[PDB]
């Protein structure tokens, strides 16, 4: 399938061309909303932890895919294996704001914490990269604190980014990167 | 939205699970994907 | 009294995918507006397919220069995602996260040299069972095609989905050095004052393409 | 037998907002009557909007006296709830409890001096990016308005809702000394035997006003 | 009444959760709020 | 409040057969195709019935050679699955897994010798209460039948389902040496130059056959 | 499929319990079982 190339209009090609047929693919899995809903366990750095995302390992699935689309929106579903009582506090709310039991001060059970989390930014949308290590103080989905937090996971929800970014991986060396799969 | 195969209204009301997306007044990437010709700039033979 | 219940053992112990949802404890939140916001998308094989990428290469450069000897083979390597040139590309910069796949992938070609540089190339595609050629002559026996520079520059060839199982893996082992999917190999016919030119090859997802079974596992 | 059940971990552990309700264990209580009881209400931005308050000030007094020199600026400060003069007012005596907001707020003016005291004032409103003026001349370049004492005394000017994000915070930091919302600034034209008079400014919620995201955090 | 997003009749009967408000025979603050004119005591120009 | 519940003791503690199903935590998986795939089946008494097997024997060989003396009895043994000759066969290579059964089983006969080898056989079936014969003469008093080699070779005789209880076990004890189901016994009339021939007997499930109550218990 | 006597939709959605068998375009052992004659290659007497 020839064409003009310095025009970059999408100009694909497919099987049929020289022969063969083309199939009915079921990409359900490469569905952006689908493969971003599944918790990421980031290090709950002490107790006073901010519900940021660029804290997460930029190498995990929900992390990586995260770092590939500039803009985005979604909600939150957390997890907190921990000690004491998780007293979350909204966005913008004073660091200190997170302490009063009246605030959503969850009461421990066994063993972590599964709760829902609205996306509460004053901006109509958020991003992993603000051209404005150096990204905005309104870029936080609330903020938690208990009295010792051991497990921090963020199941992003109702996902939906916008615009794209670069996707690369494991620089091999033999034109074919070798790594033991699952064998009998 | 990922993995929500609950048969119920996930109990807790609508205006409760997630935060409601107020309106105003692949979206586009699918728009520039579903338009790539597999034609030929000459004329097939044989 | 009240409805009895079987506190069943083993049902409900937190799963990093658990179908159900958690409990909401704030509610009644009206967000800003997300109206017709620029360049959205919701599928990664949509942008993969929709916006190709060039390939890393020997040295690093994407392009390739016309051999001026019998050694014609301009390319050649393992037809799998492990493919170093691909391992960075957009389609490869993700198939990492999915154990298997099927479908077709594309190889777009381009020239950059002068108009006084008329040239000819080739694209062979051999399978598993034998080692790739080095002579378009021996290669003209695989499923191929011939083309030559012109007015229109680009050109995208779709490479076939052939494998016993309708699938196979994106990963690889030192057991698969015989690759379950082939060794695609590009060559070079003849040319004119067209030596040392740039024939950059990119890669998108063909229509036949598909990707499944999410696997996350340390990748930077 | 009986309906199995998954004693799911993590669902139900007491939440200071938990949507559901607790159990009642007395019931069948018929209370007194609450018929047309005086001055009820059910929204705090209803009384905020509905009944303004004056502003604390230098010294403490609410009013302000006509400068009789070139120094005209009768007011000037951070356009945010942190605003000391507001920090006590009714609208400010609550925005504490809500992390963000949007909308418009109002500034009502009044005179109190003799009829032999005809006077003129000004109201400038500059934004973030520059420091407020000190010369109605330089100020007449923001979104303003001019007025002069008359028969009717009061007058309420609504100040605009301008910010990148449709929102922004009520709190503040020594990072926001550049304020994300501006430095509203009131001045003083000229006057007559109208020096030392009282121009008290109050504050209500304009119609555009809105307030959200409940945050409780130690305040006396 | 605050945060009651239960989809059921909160199980326990009506005359049980709260105590029933017997009758006899913003109510007002909304009454003196929804009546503030943004007019002009002169006449707009320009 | 919320729906009360009786955390009932004893209901839900894992059962290697538990009727209910577990929880799924991946979902949305579209498999390959299983269209008209060769020789399927879904019942083991379908292939049992549908494809017989020969019987192990003294020595090991399946067949049997024509006695050339008064000793005619070509076979004889315990009419039960424990039957060594059967214990390996397809129907027996499974009744292991089912405590009881009922129904009918079949015994197919075949010749292999020359055409100059015309021969005659017999099939007696006695029950519990007496020991099997050794003289077709004494045997011709059970429920039997006589046949002789011809054009068509094979022949399958169905042996009757007789027992007090409509059932009885597949296993056995040194208490049941009197067997609750009989001692089927095959003999040999007369013949001609048909001594030392091969009369191989196989076994399938008759139509009356049935098998129930799954029991797994160490078997190699 | 063995021992599934649940009266409900086993809660979790269809496309969730098992993996959906995409089509294309005793099956047979019952076919060669249900066809075995109990007749006689001669003719019954008595």
Image (cartoon, coloured by chain):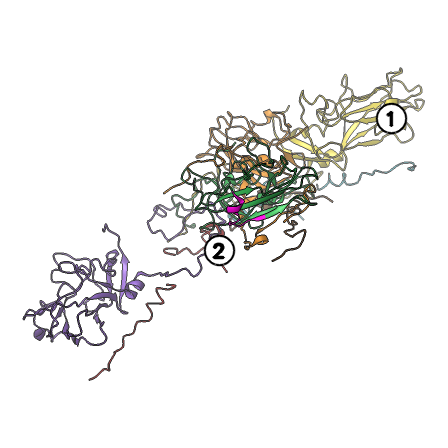
Chain colours: A orange, B brown, C green, D yellow, E cyan, F purple, G red
Q: Which chain is home to disc 2?
A: G
Query: What whole-number distance in Å separates the C-alpha atoms at marks 1 and 2?
Result: 73 Å
Which stretch appears magenta?
C135-145
Q: How many residues crowd mark 2 within 10 Å: few (<14), some (14–19), many (20+)?
A: few
User: Which of the 4 image quadrants contains residue C36?
Assistant: top right
Is E6 above or below relative to D66?
A: below
Quadrant assignment for the C terminus of chain G: bottom left
Q: Which residue is mark 1?
A: D140
- Please tell me which residue is depicted at 36% across the width and 55% down the height of the picture: G3
Residue G22, numbered circle: 2
Is F162 above or below relative to D187?
A: below
Q: Position of residue C176 (x, y in %)?
A: 42, 41
Q: Is residue A116 visible?
A: no
Can you name the residue that lies furthest to the left here? F70
Q: Secondary structure at mark 2?
A: loop
Quadrant assignment for the N terminus of chain G: bottom left
């Amino acid at each position: 399938t020839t064409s003009a190339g310095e025009s970059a209009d999408p100009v694909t090609a497919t099987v049929e061309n020289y022969g063969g047929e083309t199939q009915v693919q079921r990409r359900q899995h490469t569905d952006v909303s689908f493969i971003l809903d599944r918790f990421v366990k980031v290090t709950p750095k002490d107790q006073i932890n901010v519900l940021d995302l660029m804290q997460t390992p930029a190498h995990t699935l929900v992390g990586a895919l995260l770092r590939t689309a500039t803009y985005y929106f979604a909600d939150l579903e957390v997890a907190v294996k921990h000690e004491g009582n998780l007293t979350w506090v909204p966005n913008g709310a004073p660091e200190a704001a997170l302490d009063n039991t009246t605030n959503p001060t969850a009461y421990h059970k066994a063993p972590l914490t599964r709760l829902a989390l609205p996306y509460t930014a004053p901006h109509r949308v958020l991003a992993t990269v603000y051209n404005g290590r150096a990204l905005p103080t309104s870029f936080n989905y609330g903020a938690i604190k208990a009295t010792r937090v051991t497990e921090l996971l963020y199941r992003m929800k109702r996902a939906e980014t916008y615009c794209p970014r670069p996707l690369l991986a494991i620089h091999p060396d033999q034109a074919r990167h070798k790594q033991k799969i699952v064998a009998p | 939205s990922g993995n929500t195969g609950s048969i119920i209204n996930n109990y807790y009301m609508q205006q409760y699970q997630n935060s409601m997306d107020t309106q105003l007044g692949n979206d586009w990437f699918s728009k520039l994907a579903s338009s790539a010709f597999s034609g030929l700039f000459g004329a097939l033979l044989a | 009294g009240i409805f009895p219940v079987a506190c069943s053992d083993g049902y409900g112990g937190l799963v990093t995918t658990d179908p159900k949802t958690a409990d909401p404890a704030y509610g009644k939140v009206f967000n800003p507006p997300r109206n017709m916001l620029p360049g959205r998308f919701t599928n990664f094989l949509d942008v993969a397919e929709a916006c190709p990428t060039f390939l890393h290469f020997e040295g690093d450069v994407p392009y390739v220069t016309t051999k001026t000897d019998s050694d014609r083979v301009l390319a050649q390597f393992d037809l799998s995602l492990a493919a170093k040139h691909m391992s960075n590309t957009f389609l490869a910069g993700l198939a990492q996260y999915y154990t298997q796949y099927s479908g077709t992938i594309n190889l777009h070609f381009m020239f950059t040299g002068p108009t006084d540089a008329k040239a000819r190339y080739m694209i062979a595609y051999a399978p598993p069972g034998m080692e790739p050629p080095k002579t378009p002559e021996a290669a003209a026996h695989c499923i191929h095609a011939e083309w030559d520079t012109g007015l229109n520059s680009k050109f995208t060839f779709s490479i076939p989905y052939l494998s016993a199982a309708d699938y196979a893996y994106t990963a690889s082992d030192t057991a698969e050095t015989t690759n379950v999917q082939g060794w695609v190999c590009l060559f070079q016919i003849t040319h004119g004052k067209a030596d040392g030119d740039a024939l950059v090859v990119l890669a998108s997802a063909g229509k036949d393409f598909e990707l499944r079974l999410p696997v996350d596992a340390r990748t930077q």
